[PDB]
Image (spheres, rainbow, N blue to C red):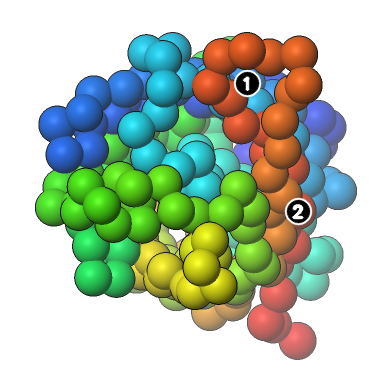
Amino acid sequence: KGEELFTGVVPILVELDGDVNGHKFSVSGEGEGDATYGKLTLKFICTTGKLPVPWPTLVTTFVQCFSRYPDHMKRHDFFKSAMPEGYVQERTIFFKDDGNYKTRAEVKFEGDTLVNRIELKGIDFKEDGNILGHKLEYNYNSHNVYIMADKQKNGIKVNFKIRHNIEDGSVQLADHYQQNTPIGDGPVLLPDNHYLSVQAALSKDPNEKRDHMVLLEFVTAAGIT
């Protein structure tokens, strides 16, 4: 079991290659993951200067193998069973009445480090919309992430909507269609339906001058008796 791999606080590296409406950018992240607790701490920096999109819009794109699966759930944990060979995470994110993000990532162990490498392509945003106009609050809400087994592809099928709060007191929904599929030949662990409970909290390093985002994530699995 790759569950034996998350026994401690694992180190995390995130590399995202990006392009939204042709605006290229790149972000690097680093931090650590305690799956036992159910907790991530990550910090990100735009290395091409300014991020052309609000930071909150990439939180879900920037490692669900650090979800805390209670003891009677531990076998619905595809995310870890797929390790250290890892898996591929593919998504489409439709921002309601605005553009979309299309992401492919590989999440696998690269030594002791758990690494998430992301290709993101984003099209059809409105330059004076909520996303390209930077009208989102620098903050994040609490969501459930709903997980189904997809034996067909022998991976999973995940869905949820993010509720991005808008300056004007409004909500911008972002609808996530997600699938994860195993990299290795050595069998993933297909789950009964459950959900992950995700609270994310967003901050700034007062000493960091580059465009960055600090992230604290708390996740714990749930739904099964």
Residue 130 image offset from top left, x and y in percent: 36, 57
Residue projecting furthest to the front: 168
Q: Is residue 159 shown above or below 208?
A: below
**Amino acid beneath label 1:** Glu
Residue 181 image offset from top left, x and y in percent: 35, 50
- Residue to which mark 2 is pinned: 218
Q: Is residue 191 left or right of residue 176?
A: right
| Residue drawn at point x = 75 percent, y = 86 percent | 225
Element at label 1: strand
Q: Does residue 82 appear in the picture of this structure? A: no
User: Looking at the image, is mark 2 or mark 1 earlier in the sequence?
Assistant: 1
For this rendering, which residue is in front, 160 or 34? 160
- Residue to which mark 1 is pinned: 30
For this rendering, which residue is in front, 115 or 129? 129
Element at label 2: strand
Q: Is residue 190 shown above or below 120?
A: below
Dividing the picture into quadrants, the one containing residue 15 is top left
| Residue drawn at point x = 68 percent, y = 44 percent | 202
Q: Which mark is residue 40?
A: none
**Amino acid beneath label 2:** Phe
Q: Is residue 35 left or right of residue 45?
A: right
Q: Does residue 207 appear in the picture of this structure? A: yes
Q: Is residue 186 left or right of residue 104?
A: right
